[PDB]
Length: 348
Image (cartoon, rainbow, N blue to C red):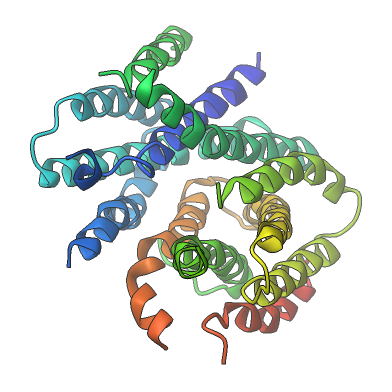
């Protein structure tokens, strides 16, 4: 009976990630400082998520999480269809903002409900690793499915008919500020670990073009690592797992950029994806453990902070891409990550 909530969270996360990733190959200018607006097109979702999550945080504790879940389903259902008839780019920006706030609400409600239903550490870790694996599956299957169905209304009909079953199942089933660094360390670690891939995402096509599917190895590694290295981390402490993951991602990021040939350039992305997935999966339940240590037993605000840290990198990663490219390696994030790694060496 308890696995129904996990299934609902899985479906919601997969749906949100699939909707997010389908926008990558198709652009409003493609279908017909322009690149600045193109970047803003996908930056708007992250910015509105960051702006909206903290305000909708405490409402979960004030009222509940099932009603926010139903509202997230409703807003997703009313927002997805609008992509079918798009007139102007500003309408696309508005649709992106609505989808972003809906995804934020759905994710926070799902994480809160999943944290509240299970009070056991290893089961909680397994459930959240399953959620992360579902996110990985969605981000992996988005682009190819969208690309193949673009040729064979048509681009989004499958999603429009898929949301219906999830909505029907969901319908049928029915202190703000912290000065403690013990959560801030995890927030910063996950923020930088996500900022690494956020910065790596747009820079690679520049090298590909100047040297004459890029994120597929990374997604494959993420999916094949998260679910397989999640549960085993409970056997021992979180020190070694997080430290090794941070060291691995730092080494991979430092070694990836320079490449004499491009055929083997995709191989380091496997290491990057494995490292980011391992770090995220290992670090996710530590916040819940700290909440259990804390007097407050409501996980809504801490998971809201976690999501804010998750989306901080997506907010303005590619904002300074051209300036960084014009600007000794162009990427130095690995050094920052490795020097910040020993901060989380000691844990309760």
